Image (cartoon, coloured by chain):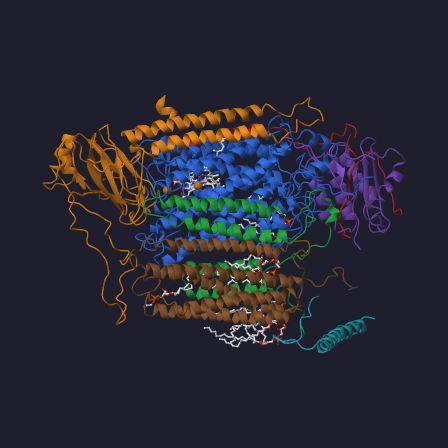
Chain colours: A brown, B cyan, C orange, D purple, E blue, F green, G red
Amino acid sequence: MTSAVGTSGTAITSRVHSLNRPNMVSVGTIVWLSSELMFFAGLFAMYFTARAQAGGAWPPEPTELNLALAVPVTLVLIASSFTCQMGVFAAERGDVFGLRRWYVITFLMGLFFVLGQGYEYIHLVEHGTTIPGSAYGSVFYLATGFHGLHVIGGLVAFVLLLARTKMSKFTPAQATAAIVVSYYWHFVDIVWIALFATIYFVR
Amino acid sequence: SGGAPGTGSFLFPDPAVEHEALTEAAHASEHKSLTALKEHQDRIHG
Amino acid sequence: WSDALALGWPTGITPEAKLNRELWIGSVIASFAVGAIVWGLIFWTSAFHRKKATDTELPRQFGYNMPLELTLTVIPFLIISVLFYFTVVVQERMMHKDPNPEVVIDVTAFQWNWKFGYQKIAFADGSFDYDGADPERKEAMTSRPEGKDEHGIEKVGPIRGMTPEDRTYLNFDKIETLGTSSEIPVLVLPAGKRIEFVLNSADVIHGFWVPEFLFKRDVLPEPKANNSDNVFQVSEIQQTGAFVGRCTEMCGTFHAMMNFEVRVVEPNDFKAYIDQRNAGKTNAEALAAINQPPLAITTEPFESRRGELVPQ
Amino acid sequence: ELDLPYGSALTSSGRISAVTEPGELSVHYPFPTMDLVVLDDALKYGSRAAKARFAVYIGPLGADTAATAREILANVPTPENAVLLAVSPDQRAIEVVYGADVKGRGIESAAPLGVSAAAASFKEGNLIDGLISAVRVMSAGVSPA
Amino acid sequence: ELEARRPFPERMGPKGNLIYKLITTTDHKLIGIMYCVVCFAFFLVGGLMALFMRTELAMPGLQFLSNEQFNQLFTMHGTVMLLFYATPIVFGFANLVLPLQIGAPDVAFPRLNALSFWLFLFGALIAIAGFITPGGAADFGWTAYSPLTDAIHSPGAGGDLWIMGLAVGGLGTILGGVNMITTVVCMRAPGMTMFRMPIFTWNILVTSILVLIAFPILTAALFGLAADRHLGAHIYDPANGGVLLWQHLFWFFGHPEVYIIALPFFGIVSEIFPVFSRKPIFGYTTLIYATLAIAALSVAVWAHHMYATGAVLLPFFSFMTFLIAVPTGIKFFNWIGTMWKGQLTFETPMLFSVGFLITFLLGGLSGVLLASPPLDFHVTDSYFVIAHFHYVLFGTIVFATYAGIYFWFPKMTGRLLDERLGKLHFWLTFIGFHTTFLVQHWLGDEGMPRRYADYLPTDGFTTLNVISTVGAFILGVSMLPFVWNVFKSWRYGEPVTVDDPWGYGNSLEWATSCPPPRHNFTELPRIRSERPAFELHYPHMVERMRAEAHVG
Amino acid sequence: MHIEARLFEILTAFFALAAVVYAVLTAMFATGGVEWAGTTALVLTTGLTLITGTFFRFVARRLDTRPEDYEDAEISDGAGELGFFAPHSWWPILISLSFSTAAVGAALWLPWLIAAGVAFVITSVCGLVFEYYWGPEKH
Amino acid sequence: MSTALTHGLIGGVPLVLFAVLALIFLTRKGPHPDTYKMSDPWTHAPILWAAEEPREVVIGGGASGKW
Ligand code: HEA
Ligand code: HEA
Ligand SMILES: [Cu+2]
Ligand SMILES: [Cu+2]
Ligand SMILES: [Cu+2]
């Protein structure tokens, strides 16, 4: 050494700049969010047909579709959206601890959403439909179940970014990472508002 | 490079004078480690 | 000239095909009249070589010609607009949807061969009070009152209340020209009637593509459920004789082995065909009863074997 | 000041970006594209057991030949250990000139023998093969250190 | 006053500078070279697969290979020509020259481009991996219609490996889509606005848009199909809504997939023209709108593949397929205006560009001839449609990829090619290709429908199959000059020292060294218009470049 | 920037136009009813370009003219320090091997290989995303 | 038909056409310049071919000849 030639705040830099420059992981996750919205368009088209097919009282007889356990976990998940947005408010202002508290409770009630969805799947498969049992049961298990895989991947992103906040100095690059995971998971629970309006309310 | 997070907890920060004492002491200990190893390396050849 | 300019169609045998072939002739005249002037543009702008006397002095360097761009953004829109209007006026003449046909053929289309129906005949000449059978359409609506558990569910079925392995679309008939793997299925049809085709497949999508009808349709598995108007009428069929019919999607492996024939006979030959089949005879016997060669004449029922290097 | 006479321009720093008319080439070396690869092999692969940048000069040197060859050894990119060969087919003059630190490293009997092993092939009429038979000889002669 | 250059450059390179650098790629350059290499390897695999099919169709028996092997053969062939040859190379030229064209130091997510490439390669291997399986790979077509793909039908392991191979390849190409759109949005040289970027990075902007539109529905369709096969999950069930549930959203992937195929090769050819016509690209803003005018409608045109099913809204998709045929006609007449009154020289990548022009012309004439549904009611799944998508699609990817290789080859490896051997390559990939597909129009119009393993001697038309075989085996020996040319143009071949080995280069790429430095640029030029390399290299030209740039 | 917002606004106008005209032209004029399978695909491709264009418009309003985007901008007007790009990294090859093991577990229906490939995906994704954040070994 | 004809055709017409196009395109003179005739004077610019052999002014010696 003499001092360094890369005399910066860290080895990691923001992504370009963000005062007169757009954040680039921001626009990267925005267009990848848009791609995953088209993935959910594939799942929605697998739902909105195979509901035009079944006529009459079309959600079939073994599907006592539970709303009294659905709307609490949607309310948990969309309040957790505001907890995650408060986490990114505490990420712009640079303290790791305001980030980590709100993302810990966001991860906890997102895990509560995943466990509530898993208990809904157990309670709806043990006295009802299976994924080879019905048309509507199969499309219910895939249109919201792979959304369960989306939200469990978002939870993996939460615990992963929390270990990342444990291991390094809070750079503006790490606030970029935090805002990126923040509105990835905001996209997850706006797609779940769409799915909960679609499956349960609108039918 | 950038290896200085908050020393506080996983949820709550420690007061700032304690953070300064911990990171200055750990930085001086790592500096003393490479200093003692470098002066031993110079003792082998010199 | 008319066959070689039409990129070698088979000539039509129904007015549907005649009018479709006239529109293809007009459209390849339009396509060659575009491609001739644009290949003229390319093989005349290949007269703009790098000239040997052309010094260190670049071309006109222009770009950005707005009125010429408006002219050649308006004229292809005129070409596709007149081609779209002729397309729609021939799209009106693909299924007139006559509620009074003359003979209805229930072309069901199973795994790797065909089966033709003769669901209904009604001559405007006055003959053939003939109808379809329908005791065979029994369901697989699995409305069992209790499943593997003991109470409450009374599980009804996967799709619309029934199992996928259902076969209630699959209409049958007394007359059935079934096609085995060594005898090609021979539909025979009266010349100059209104011949409706209702299309069903037992297993998998493929295509009712007679080459000389100049038309096809896909036998979707449950086409009423899948928004598929499978049925289409054929307006007449002028030319008699035998016509090949291929299979024009993907079925699985034995897919070129799905040929059929639509042999167009005279109406009195159609009389003597079915009235020598209501007294129950098979396909070869019924075709021998009307002085016409019984086996498939435009396609042989080719090899049940698998190759020219398999040991027989 | 003049650039390349058409199409080149010096960039925002000193790198002069030039062009090449589309069917034409860049180097225009009047030798085949395979035997000067043999020259580069004899001058890099089978030379690194001598530890000296073997320069090869083919241009004109129409002056006092030793002085104008040791002057153009001074831009060989390390002149203290470089064994330049200069040949002038306008003038028929071989001239092998050394760098400083190449001195007594098997070299005083290798320079006239290198000139002989070159000029035995130049009088046939092979420029590149003469350079190859010279650089292989001076690679066998100059000992590393 | 004189430099000190090596007589020839480094031939192979030192021992061991690439194979770890394979594993730990982060610049766009070497990743794009790897795209071009391994995808021409998959092009070789597909070409021999097609030559197996075309040995098979030469005689009317099943003389060479079976029925089932043929049905695997066209399927794996259609994928390793569409989803594992074209679909990667549309980002392979992006990783070649798009950060060079927009002034970017690297591509924007420089590990996620390695992730895109390696997910591509390990989706491609696990989709080819049906051939190790004893029942073989997918016998159902590339179209892969759902009553044939659900596990009752085609029950083998090769279809499942095909499904998850396209899952991985689709994810990798989505990730290529996001990092290319973020390069062109927010990683760009400081003097160029949106409009004086090159046309090729514009086509990859809109191409990556349509990748993000299309390919997640391929993964959604295909996760639904993997669930419907393994869990028996009734989504694509035929007595359900699930045979147009395949066709609607699969072709909603499929036709935007063939236009993410078609658009950056239009960008390649539109970059070929202004450096060999020695002049502007004609109507540059016209192309910069026409790419959107074709690609927005590419999404909304999707069901012009189910004319035969009788279950689509038929005048809507016919009208919009004519309306997607008009802006590519605009994009074409701009090219004819670009060659117009220029000083042409037909050195080899422009020669491939002109071959593309002729093939894509008469193929697109078959496009407007085929998109009208009564003219398609006989032609759906005939050989007129297979000669149509070859005579278009081969023309786009293969001819414009050979234009792209013979153009961006001296700037991605610093050495030229043999011009004579490239002209040999062109003329027997032109004569051979027209020999094997000018007759399949007349072979699909008279009856021989697609995806047949054999036909009959009492059926006619044996001579047109044997002349397609003659043409296809001219095309099979056509890349012996190509792989010989790049094989003796990397490790040997005519080097370039100065920039612009193609003179009158432009588009901000050609203002750096022919092996470009790590992070692409030692000196950027003052970007003023669409051709800033042409304005660096020709400063006296600029007033003549602008003073007559508006008349026509 | 400005022009990406206008670009995806053009794509949003056309995708919304095509979505609503496909819904109201397959409401009538079709065999059974609304197709529901390209209709919602068009509604959510309108959603795709809504998300991209709305975010680019949010950025473009909360920004000045960028010294990149400005027409007639010298290179010295925007020559600062860019952000971190990653150098050499051997994690994406491990991402692909992990996701390919998970995919061939999901193809050859091997649930042990699905779970193991997902575990390798988590491990290699951690190795990618922590790669420029592991501190030195504290001993 | 006549399997010798439709195998010799598809195996020879590619090789016949390959031989014809490779004898009309590869027998042209390439872009590479001709080898230097020794009797002709040195028309080229001066050439120094360095080595880069160990990677990173005062006189060493001398020798001469006259071919
Ligand atoms: C590179 C990929 C590519 C491209 C660019 C195309 C470009 C076109 N394709 Fe082709 N097509 C396929 C790859 C392509 N296609 C594939 C892979 C399939 C499906 C595989 C299968 O099902 O088996 C396919 C299937 C296909 C079908 C499916 C029907 C069937 O299965 O039978 C149709 C018809 O609608 C079709 C029509 C077109 C049209 C109208 C264009 C238009 O974009 C072309 C327009 C171009 C010209 C029109 C412009 C230039 C001419 C003039 C200079 C100006 C214009 C003049 C006119 C106004 C007359 N294509
Ligand atoms: C992307 C464009 C593309 C390309 C490049 C190809 C490459 C070729 N295709 Fe393929 N083709 C399709 C688009 C393409 N195809 C599509 C969309 C399908 C449909 C899939 C489906 O229907 O389901 C298809 C399937 C297909 C069929 C199937 C229709 C049927 O079964 O009836 C036919 C007809 O013969 C065909 C003709 C050819 C020909 C002659 C080539 C030629 O270019 C041949 C190329 C291969 C050689 C040039 C390589 C040379 C051989 C090597 C030198 C051998 C040695 C190499 C090893 C060392 C690795 N193609
Ligand atoms: Cu069939
Ligand atoms: Cu299409
Ligand atoms: Cu079709």
In this orientation, which residue lies closer to the viewer: E41 or F43? Answer: F43
Residue E173 seen from this side: no
Q: Position of residue C194 (x, y in %)?
A: 22, 33
For residue F63, side relative to residue F96 (left or right) = right
Q: Within the image, what quadrant is residue E491 found in? A: top right
Give the vertical position of E266 relative to F86 (above or below).
Answer: above
Q: Residue at x 44, y 28 (%)?
A: C31
Q: Quadrant of the N terminus of chain C?
A: top left
For residue E395, side relative to residue C266 (left or right) = right
Q: Position of residue C87 (x, y in %)?
A: 38, 32
Residue G40 seen from this side: yes
For residue E165, side relative to residue C100 (left or right) = right
Q: Position of residue A97 (x, y in %)?
A: 63, 72
Give the vertical position of G21 relative to F16 (above or below).
Answer: above
Q: Within the image, what quadrant is residue E443 found in? A: top left
Q: How many numbered badges does the structure rendering display?
A: 0
Q: Quadrant of the C terminus of chain C?
A: top left
In this orientation, which residue lies closer to the viewer: C55 or E205? Answer: E205
Q: Within the image, what quadrant is residue E112 found in? A: bottom right
For the view shown, which residue lies furthest in the left direction?
Answer: C279
Q: Position of residue C5 (x, y in %)?
A: 39, 24
